[PDB]
Amino acid sequence: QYPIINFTTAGATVQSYTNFIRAVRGRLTTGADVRHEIPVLPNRVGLPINQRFILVELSNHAELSVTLALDVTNAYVVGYRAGNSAYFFHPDNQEDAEAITHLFTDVQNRYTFAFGGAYDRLEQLAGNLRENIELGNGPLEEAISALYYYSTGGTQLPTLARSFIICIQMISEAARFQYIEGEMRTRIRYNRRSAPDPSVITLENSWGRLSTAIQESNQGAFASPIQLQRRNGSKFSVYDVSILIPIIALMVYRCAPPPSSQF
Amino acid sequence: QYPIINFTTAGATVQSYTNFIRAVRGRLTTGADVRHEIPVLPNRVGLPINQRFILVELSNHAELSVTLALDVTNAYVVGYRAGNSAYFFHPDNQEDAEAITHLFTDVQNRYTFAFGGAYDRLEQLAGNLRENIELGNGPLEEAISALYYYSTGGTQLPTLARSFIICIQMISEAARFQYIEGEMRTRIRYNRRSAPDPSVITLENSWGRLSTAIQESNQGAFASPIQLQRRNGSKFSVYDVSILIPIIALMVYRCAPPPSSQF
Image (tube, rainbow over all chains, first blue to last red; front, top):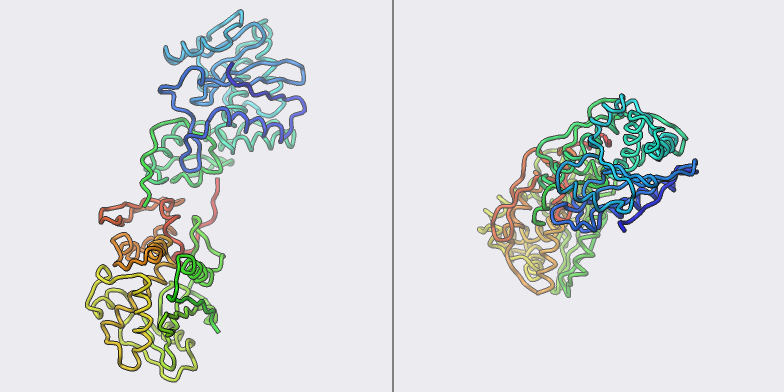
């Protein structure tokens, strides 16, 4: 079976969420590939199917559980199981449709959504942008129950889409960015629920481009800057990998690392 | 008295030269100013005279000694004492002429050369470029004796200029660059004497510009690349501070560090 990492919202603390995110990152990346102190996820090209996914079993104080499946190549959620039903985002291509047949293989009811899991899509479905969907331990407890009751009719599609938005940010994006993990740790420490500020949204939006820019940089120097936002919405220009080392924890593979070429 | 660091060529080893260079760097820089893991020398502006120099007492197997004086603001040799005579390079300006009156104050004979200590000058005087002046423990033993016999007529000006070229590279440039320290350590380990290769010459020539480029970089990214040479003469372009962290050990102060401006 693919590796499983467990997390519960019931009695969550900063340390139990930290342990969880660190365990997720350790199953996503192997150590082989670290560019500028920043690990790279495995290359999808040639990756054996037995190494392609990991599972995140989420429980809540209401004693419900769902299992999310994450693709190791991008850390993103591809689907989930609740009891005897599994649901998958619409695949991007045939190889990804075949790959997801290897997940939750004994579940009795398997479904593929006709929509994908990208935020533009999920925000249309939810009827709200990320900037208007609160994150924190209470949102996540609620999102776990909403995913669990979907197959029985208790969850309307906008709630299910909002619930995916919450899970993806609090698991996938936190795994990708220590900064976003830190914002979720602060919400647990102060028992706050609050929508993501523009620093969180622009890091999420820029993860792919930051990955490419780091990996195609000249000795760390970007060829072209990337504009992010600070918490108050003002502009932050990124010219080099160095400023991202405390921020980004993993990258999607975009090219092979150039030869070491030390002086 | 200004701090003194002792070194002898007699029975020198890789470890005794390593200890020496590390002690020199510890007296040149204080720790206050470190940009990209690379220390900065003190700013000359406002630096009290009692903090302006350090002294390097060099002895050899012939039981002769000379004392070089180094300016902490650039690590370079400003003059030297041998017994009852002291000699100083021609100062660049009035403040530097006054500053050197604070060195070797009880020496009976004080002289200022009419020439400065820059390599273009010293190579004209020596009648040879750096690329044709061997470095190593034997050159340095010889250069110490040549400096010691200058006041008595035993050293011709081209030998004295060659001897300054040897000392400046094996002390100042080795302090400035771990790479150049490493090339001198290899000469001692294998008892080799050999002229500096183009990697050593182009680092020496570029120290000032590398200092400015690092300090005025955008998060480590140079605005304009710096071309160096590898040992075989071929071109090496530097686009970022990261590649220099194993190479350059100290920099001349060129600007104040911008605000931390972390994300």
